[PDB]
Length: 124
Length: 124
Length: 124
Length: 124
Ligand SMILES: Nc1nc2c([nH]c(=O)n2[C@H]2C[C@H](O)[C@@H](CO)O2)c(=O)[nH]1
Ligand SMILES: Nc1nc2c([nH]c(=O)n2[C@H]2C[C@H](O)[C@@H](CO)O2)c(=O)[nH]1
Ligand SMILES: *[C@@H]1O[C@H](CO)[C@@H](O)[C@H](O)[C@H]1NC(C)=O
Ligand SMILES: *[C@@H]1O[C@H](CO)[C@@H](O)[C@H](O)[C@H]1NC(C)=O
Ligand SMILES: *[C@@H]1O[C@H](CO)[C@@H](O)[C@H](O)[C@H]1NC(C)=O
Ligand SMILES: *[C@@H]1O[C@H](CO)[C@@H](O)[C@H](O)[C@H]1NC(C)=O
Image (cartoon, rainbow over all chains, first blue to last red; front, top):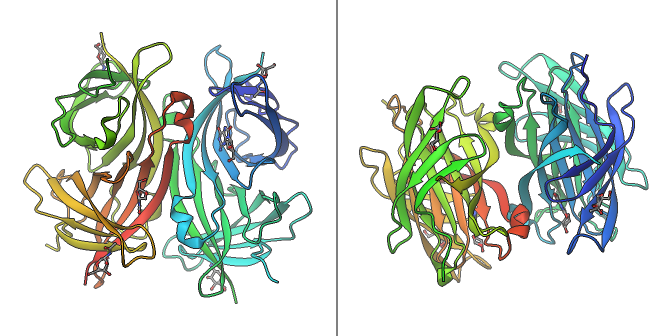
């Protein structure tokens, strides 16, 4: 019965925050992503996110992915991971991400993608 | 003058094909992703995708990200890359992807993520 | 003044431990990587590693990469990261890794690579 | 019998070249990596590489990994992949890589790792 659900307010290991609304019945959802550019406490930015969670076998702990469309740069980041209910134990989203920068020349493509992780917990 | 445009029919280096529809003014779009099994010859699965293309500075070669919500498994894949005008004049999407599998215990999280690339060109 | 030094005994966020020996003047080094199975409790496998640490500008927090040649499978893992002095003063290696599995046909290449992270701290 | 062997001279999809010497009986090997920084035809640089190939079940087509210790930067890149003998069909190494940059502050770690691929063919 214990459905790990993406809807709500989350924060992460770098101190960025994220809010995701209601997941409709085809798994779609939208959110906002707020990020720490600086000392962390002054300059904030909001960017939209859009994703889908997988509904195959109505899992507790489904996998999901979403795209963050940076409002302050020409970059795009995509996240994928899984909503786990560890013991008790908050909910926790374990994610991996790819950050695509824009390059002017296709000869620079090879260097345009960063990778990393994010762990998200419910915001308090 | 012409730009690189996600809208249309695409194919890739693995033989999978993808159709993307119109890109609205927020950069959102929807589409379909077809791939195949065995000796790539008969059974074709279709899965929807949703993503966004970065609109910051209305670039001619925009970055973008999308999420593929697999119809036939518990998995999710995210793609991000850039729509280039190649040196030979043809549109190409250079992407990288993260394929997240569903695991059962959070202790298996470590091994749930594959990474790789796809290069898409227009279909005839 | 003290720098961050790969030489020594290390442990990580998954419970695996690693020993690295002396780093010669070319930046080369060797060591051992131990991990475990089931409920992480009894059977420990040991595999050798070899790598190099970047020496350009004799930095105090050098980047490095190493290859783990698994003793118990056909697989290979590579790690790369950086040896930091953390904010709390303790040495930490932040790494990312690519785990390549062996496949049989070149058509399965696409799915042979996992990615993720490990964070190492010194053992007592 | 057809052993895909790392020893030799290779080139890649970006026009970098690589030479690897003899693989000893524990799988170790060393090489040089020559890279195109510019128009491709003028400024060359050589950097050492060191790796191991997996010897578990003496495979044709073993997996391998290696570290390239950049001589002209504080970065490190690691490659992992597999030596395939496709039909006939050259030998071909399909690789993935992680490029670690040096960051001054551990607060920048998250952005320090790029990922991508390289396909290598025997040099002619
Ligand atoms: N992809 C990604 N981007 C991030 C994270 N945190 C963060 O601040 N960013 C911003 C940094 C960069 O300035 C911007 C696009 O260049 O994305 C983050 O965790 N992931
Ligand atoms: N990791 C990696 N690095 C490369 C490749 N090609 C290339 O020229 N480099 C260089 C570029 C960069 O200037 C240097 C270290 O910063 O590594 C490459 O294919 N992979
Ligand atoms: C996240 O939320 C809290 C306020 O509830 C705050 O510490 C911080 O400003 C937020 N982080 C960002 C990047 O805005
Ligand atoms: C992709 O489309 C082409 C039609 O141009 C078709 O020949 C091919 O089999 C398709 N591949 C898949 C997996 O749908
Ligand atoms: C790592 O080392 C510690 C000793 O400090 C031990 O308790 C632990 O079980 C070891 N883990 C493995 C997998 O070797
Ligand atoms: C690779 O080798 C050939 C010469 O055989 C040449 O085209 C090129 O200069 C080499 N590439 C680099 C980066 O040196």
